[PDB]
Length: 60
Length: 109
Image (cartoon, rainbow over all chains, first blue to last red; front, side):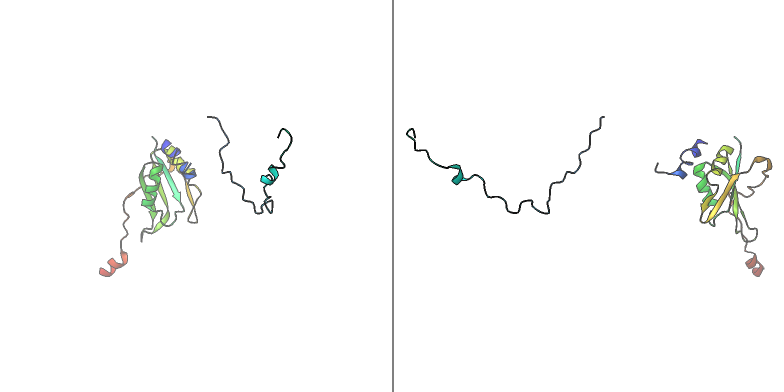
């Protein structure tokens, strides 16, 4: 009788039937609609601001 | 052990002797099967009696296909106890029923 009890009785009720780390998930990169600064600032330390003055002291 | 006999009622047009045998076989082996048919034209009476080797197998079907909505028909099957089973529910069972062409044989005769 077990022939029909299993896989003939339950087929009529459906035939198809160590540690955990957070999985890696697709981390997208920024694609801003607006660049947050209109005009990129001109360089802040160039030659004409690095060298300010020569010293002409007696040791110099 | 004990010869289980089963009745099936409200047969959809098509659920005939072969179709039932190839269906109930996977439930379990079926020995003697007859389906009541018209005496004259051999048309279906839409109810059949089947036998199972064990009443336990015979009662298996009675709790699944009972009230089985099929093609708009509610199949009626339940175990018929052996006290009132007659001798020949399976007289001519598993035999292609003979429908004789009464009209044509009359014209030839």
